[PDB]
Image: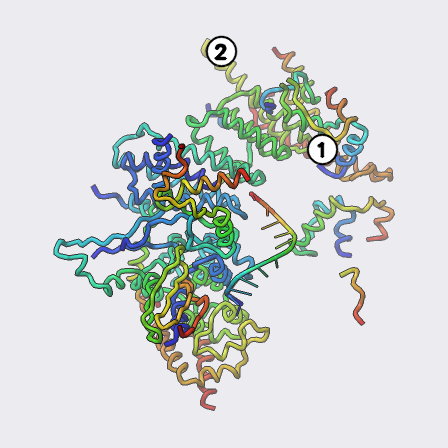
Amino acid sequence: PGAGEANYDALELNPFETKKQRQEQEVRTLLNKLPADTITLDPNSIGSVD
Amino acid sequence: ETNLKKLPKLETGFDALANDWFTLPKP
Amino acid sequence: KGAAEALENANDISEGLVSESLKAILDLNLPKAKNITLAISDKNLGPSIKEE
Amino acid sequence: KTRYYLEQCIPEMDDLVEKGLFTKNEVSLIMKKRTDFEHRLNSRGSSINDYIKYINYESNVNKLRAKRCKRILQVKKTNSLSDWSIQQRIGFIYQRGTNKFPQDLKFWAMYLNYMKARGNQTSYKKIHNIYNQLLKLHPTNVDIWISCAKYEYEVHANFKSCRNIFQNGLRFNPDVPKLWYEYVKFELNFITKLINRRKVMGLINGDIALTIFDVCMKTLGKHYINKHKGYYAISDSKMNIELNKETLNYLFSESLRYIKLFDEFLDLE
Amino acid sequence: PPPDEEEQLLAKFVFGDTTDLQENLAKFNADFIF
Amino acid sequence: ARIILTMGIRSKASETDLSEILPEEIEERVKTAAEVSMGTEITQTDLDNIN
Amino acid sequence: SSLSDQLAQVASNNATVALDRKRRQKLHSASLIYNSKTAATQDYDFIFENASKALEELSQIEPKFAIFSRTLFSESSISLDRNVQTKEEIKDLDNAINAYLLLASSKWYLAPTLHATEWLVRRFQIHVKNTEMLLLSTLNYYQTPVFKRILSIIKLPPLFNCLSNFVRSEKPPTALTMIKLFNDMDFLKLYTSYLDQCIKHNATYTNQLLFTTCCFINVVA
Amino acid sequence: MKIKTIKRSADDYVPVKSTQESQMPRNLNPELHPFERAREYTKALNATK
Amino acid sequence: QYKKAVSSAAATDYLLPESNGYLEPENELEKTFKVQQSEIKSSVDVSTANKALDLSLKEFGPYHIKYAKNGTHLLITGRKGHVASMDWRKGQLRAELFLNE
Amino acid sequence: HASAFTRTQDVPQTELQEKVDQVLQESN
RNA sequence: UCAAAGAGUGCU
């Protein structure tokens, strides 16, 4: 008891994802691919003003 | 007052309602 | 109401005339109101509507 | 946009939990049933029974809140969003269902009755707005013209506008004999109450119907000639006689029906 | 004070309680139905 | 043919009862067809021989 | 055991879970009144409404049907799912279903029984879980169209493999194929228990006995 | 003793109707949606293109 | 707007349909470590008992288990080289690899 | 907005109306 | 049958 998360966000991941949306999710996440050089020690640091 | 009750009330039903030709033969 | 009304209105629509049915339906809908604007396919029907 | 509807209700459950009426567990159950309906109503193949089911389910939630208010808070009304929100939202669902399915006269009927019962909460102007759309969508249904005429001659007793509703209805439906009968019946009702008031006035100190009779024959005859003849006139001289006879037979039964109306009114001569 | 039967009946409908059904199950005996 | 005996003209079709002739679902079709019908009016001189 | 064999047991255990849209279509499409397309469109509430009326007609013919209105054909049964119930409750649910099949034993010729059973098929999926009890009870309604509809929507158990020919078939099962079913030793004693239940309950009726008598008499020949 | 486990109602998440829209559960827990700052930027850059 | 935005986040926290599990003892004598796994198998419903999976196979032991993010599909790889991809809920194997590496 | 309740025509459109208001005018 | 891939139809 308590091992898993109580509630899951549909947009991020869905156990009930049908065959056609998992493709819809796949292409979108490709479109939203994060560059390798975007990696940082803190996600909040990125985008500051120099 | 008794007469006023005898007078008719307009009756309405909505409240009651509330409660192929072109195909040739194959040889 | 029936077949007869459609023909006599069909006669009236063609001659750019306003039937009692057209006068009846329009009155309940278009506000008295600056001037309310109504779209009609017929230019000839326009003057008839304006008169009424 | 199901989430938008779900989010509009958040302040209310928070109010339910804050007041202590409903536990977070019970509140979650109400939410889950609410969520299923909203997706149902917004989806494809949605029907009116979905609106009725949601309205019936939501009505029950209001009753439990009222019972729990006296049981737990021991208050008739707690001054917070909870009191008027379930009642407000039900009207919203009626608007959507009536908007979504204008055809069903049955669904419109509960909407008028539901708002009529909560007379204090819903102004008579809101009942007016519902009728104006309803008469506008279904102008040829006599029952609705007599509907709003009956509502306000009894609840509001405005004979001038009650005359107006019939005055409009007869314009669209001059061939239905039922509508003429009610507008005559209303007319003699107005006269009798006026005369009875005059009698009461003395104690503390009609032709107009017959005119409605006159034209009522003429147009009913005209329309009955228009029907049974179809698009065109009848060439044979004999049939035109039966056409006249049929109107006379149809017309007399219309007149005889009114002779029975006169008997009901004792005061009138 | 404990709720009245009328209040109890309304409680089951709103909360969707299925216990009442469950003992009515757990108390069936096939002999009685036949 | 039995329909023509009961109703001579489409105007009669609207009120004439076809229960003994046709089932409920069919008999209403002819009534609806009658008012949206296509044929022209026929004389009683004509109607007599058709009967 | 092979992983595929172990995996097959998992599928059988979760046959009714309805993980996705595609499985739910197969479960809900199964129907005894309507075709697959119309069946998918129908609602539990709509199905329950017809079933409740059907049970009342059955109640008039025999009062004992009225008991299930309190248990199986209740309004709360709409919200009852078996997948969410525990072991004790499922055993508790199954027996109540079994008695209903027994009381319906002499009445499938009556149309309302077919409507009433639809709720159990749609809500409780008796065709998937209580597949033996449903099919044992309808053995002597074989030539009736109802039995053919049962075969289409039902996965035949191992003991009824001989009927796999007539599933979704124009011709109904012949009388000769039956002897083969009862000729099987494992079936007779399976059939013995069900008959043993009816005699205890006095639920046996003529058409059960007369169908029952011939086949065993035929197995001898 | 008292046990409760994460329990999914199949009817809630998989509609009985073929035409009814499946429920999309949503949780705005910030941890469940990582890389805000990289994400919005990528949606920004795609928009300019 | 942040105090408004977090308020909206607090608003959606109510929307979340279900909660996590618990396991606390009724009696202080009862201990969460004392409870044995079979007893929990009894408490959980039938579907959860099916959701629990146990398969014994020794051909390519040991086997490393990996779990998909969405979690529909299990990937288990044997030490001697056997890997099978399958969905535990559905009960269908996606692909079978018998490579002896 | 146009409503069946209040007359926006300002004159009697139907022959009924020309007649009824005459009685209303004649009465008082 | 499942299972992966296309191409049209209805409708929010």
Residue occupying the point 77% across, 27% down: C43
Q: Chain of mark 2?
A: D
Q: Amino acid at mark 1?
A: Leu
Q: Which callout, 2 or 1, points at the residue further toward the start of the chain? A: 2
Residue at the extreme front: A50
The answer to whether the residue labelled 2 contacts the one labelled 1, judged by CB atoms less than 8 Å apart, is no
Q: How many marks?
A: 2
Q: Amino acid at mark 2?
A: Gly
Residue occupying the point 43% across, 62% down: G120
The residue carrying mark 2 is D202
Q: Chain of mark 1?
A: D
Residue occupying the point 31% across, 53% down: A4
Residue C19, percent from left and from top: 75, 28
Residue C34, percent from left and from top: 64, 17
Q: Which mark is residue D251?
A: 1
Q: Secondary structure at mark 1?
A: helix
